[PDB]
Image 1 (cartoon, each protein chain N blue to C red):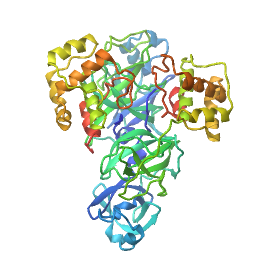
Image 2 (image 1 turned 60 degrees about the vertical axis):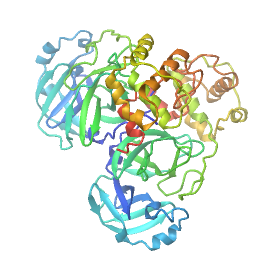
Image 3 (image 1 turned 90 degrees about the vertical axis):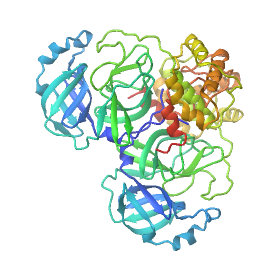
Image 4 (image 1 turned 180 degrees about the vertical axis):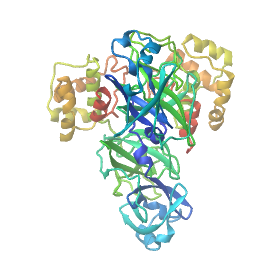
Length: 300
Length: 302
């Protein structure tokens, strides 16, 4: 198994840079709109307690420097939607792919294209933690970098980068400017809540182990969803939702192992450990491979 | 700190589909030449023991179906360079980036753009193991996928995929068709030499663990370079050269730990183990991060 990003070319052709004053961050150029974090309009002094509405009325279209490479795109309109600034430009991006804006659930994975001054720098796979942070690599200048999934040439944009917390994890919004988690875009003290293990992803990882012939951990037991949920939280695991059981369906069908039987197998691992043994060459359970990631790597 | 591949857009624009007989795989389209693994001309029975020069002379340009997305490209010439086939086409790739063919050294890393039927599907980092295999993710149809590094706007192609060994590791060639390792393009069981751990990479990754706040493995002790290499050879780690020591300099200076100080810490880890602890989340010593990979993601912003 390997963490695998989506090919980043379709997103690369949409990365621009947006500058106000001396603050330059990344923007996403789709059709004739550029999307970027709204704190590009902030000086450092009012970053402490931004009145974004008041700061925005004092800004005009001519205050925004949008550049594809070093080519300026003229701004003809500006608006603010939640924590995201939308800059209408006079040129429709000829590299605009088929796209959607979606809001992902915790545990879902996506590829991040880390950018600096509009230039793509690297691509890697992230998982949205249950505490709504991501463990990624975001240096200063990465604000405005986006996270995405691709399904049949359609780019689902799901993340835009805004913030790094004291513990080094990162936080941001969807493409409608709504933060994942209880974070606000201001230089104040903010803390990530306590994180938990993504149970649906651990179950997917166990299914991948079974597909590969590593199945010593399968037991004769079963369980109810509610009983597993109550036991799992005692080990700081996420409770399983409706959609979690459903998205495990394909793997349950591929292996013939009922979802609730696999839950009983994971429950035994939590209660008794792995008594020295290994799973897919590891005495650690992995929780950042989704069921879709599993079919994408075990199957075609 | 995590494995980061280069943006793949420049390579995606070069991937095409190449078909000969019942075999479909990927090709790399640069200027008016498409490069692809030469076993695309082999039937499944040819695969068992091919005489490649003989099998090629019996092929015509028209036996090669090349597809770039929806459009077919006409083959007007074909030649063979070692294990790589070069198909000349009537059209030049307008998306051809500035590029080079390089053969990388063991221990170095590169980004792999996994492709199927000429369509890119994923991108990830791989390291050329000392035994000249790579631990990749390649399924049926991934042959012709390339590995590369990007410096500014220059794509340095270094790998093209050919094979999966019985152990699950992968083997391929450079873009001149020469295999990494003692492998040959045949349907015959082949094992690799004994793999060793990339020592200079483990140290850089231990440094990254400190730039990122994890210091538990350190110790107040030190070691000579030769005494470290004696222990390292015992545990099947590659030797650490003075060139390796110099390369870790920026990482050593960026933190407060001399290289030989970190060598003493690695020596202790190899002699005791990690006693159920983790380093950067991992339960094992990672060796697929080069010192260059560490400096870029630890305050590099490139």
